[PDB]
Length: 122
Length: 122
Image (cartoon, rainbow over all chains, first blue to last red; front, side, top):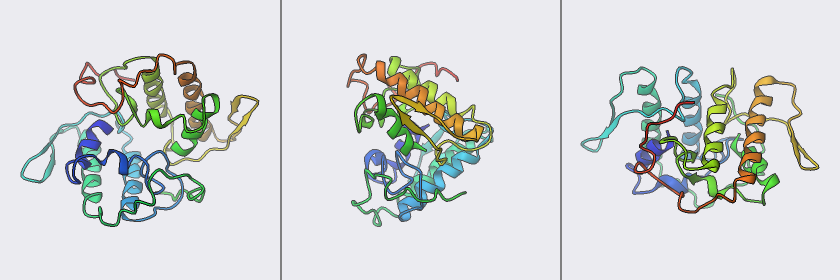
């Protein structure tokens, strides 16, 4: 779930991904329409597919087990699906980390006039 | 997609009347656990638990066709998958309407000391 996912980004990028990413590019927050505006975006985009493909469980509901040990985030659920929701969020918070510098404070709290375009398939 | 969800929510309520669900309670936006905190929250649950019924296509990246006529979100679309989604936004958007009075800011941006309950399943 997001509770779990936010704490993961917020543990790779300072202490509150919830905001910058609550509505960024075209696929970061309350959106999901158009084409990725940049790193953070190709990420937020790639995240929801990753979520999408998990058909076995409910990515938005799944409560998985994880730990931030050594500066590395590890997943601890065996349930092959729960181990995925985590891997997706996990990678996601690494995606949002190594690209924090591409962040354009000019793309958050987005409209959709800038994304009314094609919601690229995945 | 959530762009449209921001849009449909506003129709009964006021424009931009959605920032208060970006993170509200246990389910509205970033969240997904510990059973609701009130009517509002549940709509955010029932809405979550709604996309999971979507057989086929994904709810967050799918743009549907819809029109707001004389105060009625009419989902006019010839694709059951897509139509469905719209209906998860119609029913919900109508839900939060009437439940904006049980509203309490003290259910905003929350964590795992309020939603650690026996996580109600869909």
